[PDB]
Amino acid sequence: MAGNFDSEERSSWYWGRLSRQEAVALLQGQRHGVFLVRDSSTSPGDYVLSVSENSRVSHYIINSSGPRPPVPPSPAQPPPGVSPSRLRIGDQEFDSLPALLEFYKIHYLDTTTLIEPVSRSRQGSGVILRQEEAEYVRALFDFNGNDEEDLPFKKGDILRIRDKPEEQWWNAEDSEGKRGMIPVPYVEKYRPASASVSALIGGN
Image 1 (cartoon, rainbow, N blue to C red):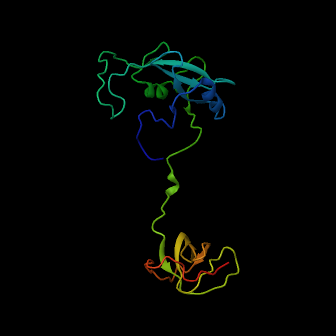
Image 2: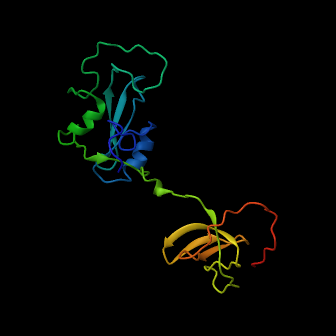
């Protein structure tokens, strides 16, 4: 998780509209009590709630007004300024659409109740991609090589820690281009730059 960003949360229930078949296609793929929302394929300016009921997934047309701007951008677009309830679905009334999914969770739409957002996949993770620096170390030992995983480098070779599994061996690219283990407990932080014409190069 990341926190509070979208009062309606797009990656949760409202992705970016499509055809009931599409929503359905994914909906059924999730938990039986899963339901997502789509765009009013019938109405020009309205929302639609989709719900995997029984074997398929039915839709519920929502009616939105829009009293205030939706997104920060947009040069100028004067809003209505009258629609009180603004958003509503079925034969009842609610403040907004996002809020609707939070109340009907136990009110029962037309036969089925709302439980959680479909969420087919994707999530704010980013797999914490560091990639901090890279080329800034000069090996201090020569070795022909025995294992494909071990980085065979020659004394004075400026490698780049391609990763750092543990403090007892890291990953780095050698003058040849291959990677492997490197001296994490003792390496030469040697600023490489002056030739770039390959002096010798002889690994495999």
